[PDB]
Amino acid sequence: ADLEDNMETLNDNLKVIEKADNAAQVKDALTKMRAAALDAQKATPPKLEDKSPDSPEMWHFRHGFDHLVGHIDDALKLANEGKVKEAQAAAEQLKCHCNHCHQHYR
Amino acid sequence: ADLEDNMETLNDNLKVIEKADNAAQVKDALTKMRAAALDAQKATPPKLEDKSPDSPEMWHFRHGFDHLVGHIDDALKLANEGKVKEAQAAAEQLKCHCNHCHQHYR
Ligand code: HEC
Ligand code: HEC
Ligand code: NI
Ligand code: NI
Image 1 (cartoon, rainbow over the protein chains, first blue to last red):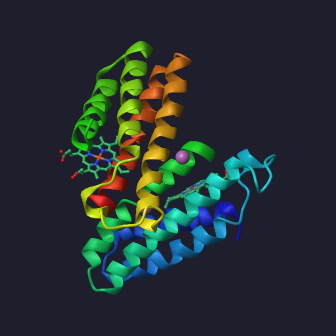
Image 2: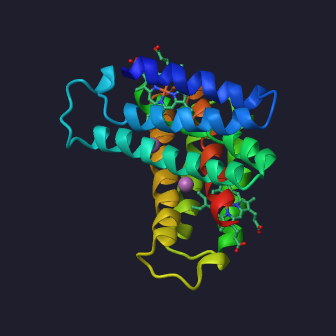
């Protein structure tokens, strides 16, 4: 899968969590988001195609996925503890991670 | 200044920027936010007193302020270009940083 695919997965599944018709859909969507974020961390965004892997722009891009994965894991822990409403509230706060990275690099 | 006064400065100046309609107003408010964030960048929240300076929790707290200052700096550059509406949109996006740190450490 490519970066565009990963971003579609992130977008669809964030919306799944918001509209989840049952509690179990939340964990499943978070699981897919986690994998998409780790896959996207290994891509080069078009606006950074000139930059080397050691460039500060690429460093911040990769770090954004690490941080998103950490907050996905926090929400997964809540869901796995049965605190699914808390997990859904935590998932809503993931949008700020999308917005921040996009501000820089989308 | 203390943490609570620094936080009040950030809180009030976000609204100053939203209320503004010219580049000088936005620049002046962003400059005040920058000074507040810096004054608190080296401090320690109550819930982290018993933590090493290099602990993961302290490191994430400090990265919170460093990253907020970076995005204030980016919004300042927009104001300095006369890009009032873009600077205001960047300022509104700062709220993600506020809520992210609070949810971890408030
Ligand atoms: C960087 C660390 C990112 C994070 C976190 C998220 N996204 Fe992203 N996104 C990023 C880039 C660099 C791009 C541009 C990709 C390109 O090839 O142009 C995008 C793009 C999107 C898109 C549009 C995809 C397309 O087909 O053009 C969507 C729908 C999208 N991103 C969604 C999305 C969501 C919902 C995120 C949070 C859960 C998210 N992204 C995180 C970089 C980064
Ligand atoms: C961590 C890196 C933070 C960032 C970024 C922001 N804030 Fe914050 N805030 C933080 C702490 C640890 C605290 C509590 C301090 C304590 O000793 O309890 C706060 C508190 C506030 C408050 C309430 C003030 C009070 O006296 O309780 C407000 C109104 C506030 N913070 C606003 C605010 C805004 C608008 C921010 C972004 C622009 C922001 N904070 C960032 C830690 C951190
Ligand atoms: Ni975090
Ligand atoms: Ni950033």
